[PDB]
Amino acid sequence: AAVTQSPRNKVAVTGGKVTLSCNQTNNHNNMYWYRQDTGHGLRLIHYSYGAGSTEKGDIPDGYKASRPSQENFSLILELATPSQTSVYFCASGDEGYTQYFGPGTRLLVLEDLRNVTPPKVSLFEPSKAEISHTQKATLVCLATGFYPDHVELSWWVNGKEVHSGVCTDPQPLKEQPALNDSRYSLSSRLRVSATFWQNPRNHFRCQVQFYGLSENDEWTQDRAKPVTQIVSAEAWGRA
Amino acid sequence: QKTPQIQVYSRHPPENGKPNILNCYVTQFHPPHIEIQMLKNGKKIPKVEMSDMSFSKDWSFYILAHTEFTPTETDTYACRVKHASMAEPKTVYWDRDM
Amino acid sequence: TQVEQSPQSLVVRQGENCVLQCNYSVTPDNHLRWFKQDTGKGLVSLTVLVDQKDKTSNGRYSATLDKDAKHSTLHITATLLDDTATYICVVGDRGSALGRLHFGAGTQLIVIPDIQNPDPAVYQLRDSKSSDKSVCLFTDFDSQTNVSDSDVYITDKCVLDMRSMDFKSNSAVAWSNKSDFACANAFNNSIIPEDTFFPS
Amino acid sequence: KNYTFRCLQMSSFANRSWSRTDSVVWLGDLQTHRWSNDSATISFTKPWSQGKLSNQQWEKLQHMFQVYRVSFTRDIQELVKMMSPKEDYPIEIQLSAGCEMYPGNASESFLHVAFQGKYVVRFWGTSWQTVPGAPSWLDLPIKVLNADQGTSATVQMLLNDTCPLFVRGLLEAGKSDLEKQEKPVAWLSSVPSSHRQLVCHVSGFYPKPVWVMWMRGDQEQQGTHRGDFLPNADETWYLQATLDGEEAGLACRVKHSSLGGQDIILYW
Ligand SMILES: CCCCCCCCCCCCCCCCCCCCCCCCCC(=O)N[C@@H](CO[C@H]1O[C@H](CO)[C@H](O)[C@H](O)[C@H]1O)[C@H](O)CCCCCCC[C@@H]1C[C@H]1CCCCCCCCCC
Ligand SMILES: *[C@@H]1O[C@H](CO[C@@H]2O[C@@H](C)[C@@H](O)[C@@H](O)[C@@H]2O)[C@@H](O[C@@H]2O[C@H](CO)[C@@H](O)[C@H](O)[C@H]2NC(C)=O)[C@H](O)[C@H]1NC(C)=O
Ligand SMILES: *[C@@H]1O[C@H](CO)[C@@H](O[C@@H]2O[C@H](CO)[C@@H](O)[C@H](O)[C@H]2NC(C)=O)[C@H](O)[C@H]1NC(C)=O
Ligand SMILES: *[C@@H]1O[C@H](CO)[C@@H](O)[C@H](O)[C@H]1NC(C)=O
Ligand SMILES: [Cl-]
């Protein structure tokens, strides 16, 4: 009974068209678009009783809705404003009361895209001192110099994602707390047993998913276009 | 849209000069929005008691209007009805011997 | 609002129980649903209560509903680190698609893990691709608060769980681009235990 | 002996914003309750309208009707959104629910719904269903309504249990008004016709079962025509009888339960 959303994470500018899509293959007649903000419950923006029809929710202003088919419900922000920076959830349901919620979409609307920058990523190898003292080994990851703070960090061992022994900072920190549109840094850790790290066959990688400009957006500045991209660092284990 | 049917009748035997009650029974209409007036010589009688609108088993709405009146030889009494089904409002006159 | 949750936020130690409240004025009140939401994540349904006087159970979670009192509680028995999340009360005003859901603002839960074997230490870790760049890792400490020069960056504490080993540890990362910065002088701006390990 | 109890509801929806619901309740042909759109509370129109129910019992019954009216209004409005543009305003729903009381302490309940003046939907057993003739698009509203298990459980409890229990209470409490006997008054008149048409007006009788016939002595006139039973304001009945000459000899005879056997004959 899955409900999919795209994009999962989007950076847009004031005045641009922003289309958030929702997809369900459950043949559900009914679909609903909500937004979540801190200190508030989820609030209905628009909903749809079937293909080719939309109805206004509690907070519809600024949004237009589209139901091209049974499968897809879209939220369209024609002229995006900063006040629409929010998390947007989509849901579907049949005749029953249960609404099935999608993964959620994080939208951020900036005044200017001139400051969008991808991260540098570095992987720091465990100290031999920790290996001797605890028989455990900590890998540290570092993402630096990115803007805005919309990144997803994950660890990969032998091409497969790990969660055990992982902890990433709840929030990124500002590199220039004095400056207004300061670039951010993020830290994360992966702790394994020394015997797991000492294996030359284990490939360790730290992956940062960065959300920035798209192929639609324009760019004039001298440095490379800061598009949505992945930046990673890797290291193999060693004796 | 179904047109109303109007029926005017006395509560007691009509005698010239004696106090009586005049009924106007409007039936068989749809939609339920309706305006009923009871008239004396062509002027609207104030304070006409109106019963609560209801419907019959065949889903036909009905409403009973009534007022106090004393009939006299020349005095003309009528029930005027406005409904969405008819273009001009319908008036039917009370005939004592009818 | 029509759905009110209490408390706004709370902090519990591992293994302690907690009770979250929900009070509502929604008419009618067909069913009540409790959601768990991890930070930056989606909505996971924990339970849905339906009757006039209702009670439900889902492992360590259990919930009550009293429709006359328009009141619901969520009990979490023997809390674990994984319970760190926001918990959301939702009231549905119909037992069909014609209904509208009424969402509460949520209750933040933070669970503090117990460290059975603390071993405070500061290690220096070197870049895999450029050995000149390095970080300092403060790790394996207990319930200690470490504070945050302008060009020195220090992260807040963070707890990892090695699930298959059943081992949990705290850590903080410090790095600085400035010269004359070392790991020995990295966390002296913080109150660190006397027997913290410092290797050569 | 067989009384039919009726809760009649009439709801009008003019557009997306404007709406109205008014109700009336009849025990046989006597009005017991009224519920105007203006009123938050159901009104009593007889001293015994509460039946044998306690004050706490009545309030509990009223509260769910209050919640019902508000919810009903919203549910229709949402169903219109769901069916658009196939169906649109203005919209009239008529609702008819109650039960017919029988000998031997038994009953049979009903819930009938009309759309734009035509019967389309009933509640039967454990679910809503459409009746023969109804348009096929109703299958979706009914599907959605049947999804609502709580509404279904309540309606079942009301029709199977609450309604019959309540009516037996009314019959005990309103016995004197229900078994009331009112004497008819008769007056005669004539109007020209396509021979003259003699009219026998009979007014002020209760109960409704009446017998009116024109008679030439003993010979009951075959050409007698009974009209419609027309209500009076004071909860009595009016009826006229016509015969289509030579008027000297014939009389209007009236049989009724109130007269105690002795009929009244009224000679021209
Ligand atoms: C009946 C005899 C009992 C004794 C009466 C005592 C005398 C007192 C006189 C009372 C005077 C009132 C007169 C009113 C007429 C009778 C009323 C009909 C029978 C009563 C029905 C009440 C139903 C109670 C349940 C209720 O209120 N449901 C509410 C609220 O339900 C929610 O809250 C409940 C809380 O109790 C539950 O949790 C439920 O799960 C949830 O969904 C629901 O919204 C149901 C409202 C509508 C249900 C019935 C719909 C009727 C629709 C019209 C028929 C079918 C549709 C056909 C029309 C076509 C559609 C048009 C639009 C499409 C273009
Ligand atoms: C309520 O009674 C019905 C049957 O009674 C009929 O429907 C009522 C609403 C009313 O109109 C009565 O006069 C009718 O005689 C029960 O419905 C039956 O339920 C069983 C089991 O659920 C099912 O197998 C049968 O098919 C149903 N019968 C019919 C005719 O549909 C219902 O269970 C009763 N509800 C409660 C709560 O007791
Ligand atoms: C019938 O009653 C309903 C409910 O009492 C009325 O709806 C209210 O309308 C006013 C203004 O028109 C609003 O302020 C309220 O919010 C409404 N209440 C509800 C519960 O919807 C309705 O106006 C009445 N109908 C008519 C024709 O007067
Ligand atoms: C709705 O209908 C009412 C009553 O007929 C009318 O007065 C009003 O103008 C209408 N309102 C809208 C918004 O259509
Ligand atoms: Cl894992």
Image: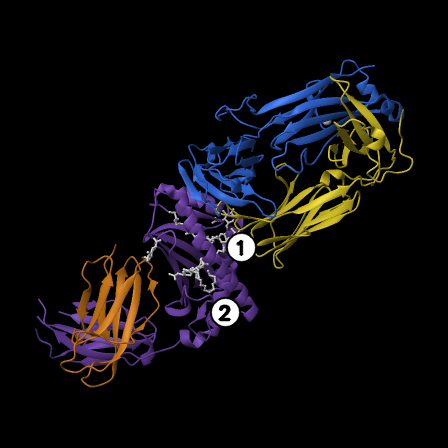
Chain colours: A blue, B orange, C yellow, D purple
The picture quadrant where one finds residue B36 is bottom left
Residue A146: percent from the left, percent from the top?
A: 63, 29
What residue sits right under mark 2 in the picture? D169
- Which residue is rendered at x = 82% and y = 25% of the image? C124
* Residue at 50% across, 64% down: D62
Q: Determine if the C-beta at disc 1 is less than 8 A from ligand 1.
A: yes
Q: Would you say B55 lies left or right of A113 here?
A: left
Query: Outermost residue, front direction?
Result: C179
Q: Which residue is label 1 attached to?
A: C28
Q: Secondary structure at mark 2?
A: helix
Residue B83 horizontal/vertical position (percent):
24, 61
Looking at the rendered structure, the kind of residue marked 1 is: Pro
Q: Nearer the viewer, residue D13 or C2?
A: C2
Extreme-bottom residue of the structure = B17
Chain letter for mark 1: C
Disc 2 packing (10 Å; few <14; some 14–19; many ≥20): some
Displayed quadrant of residue B26 = bottom left
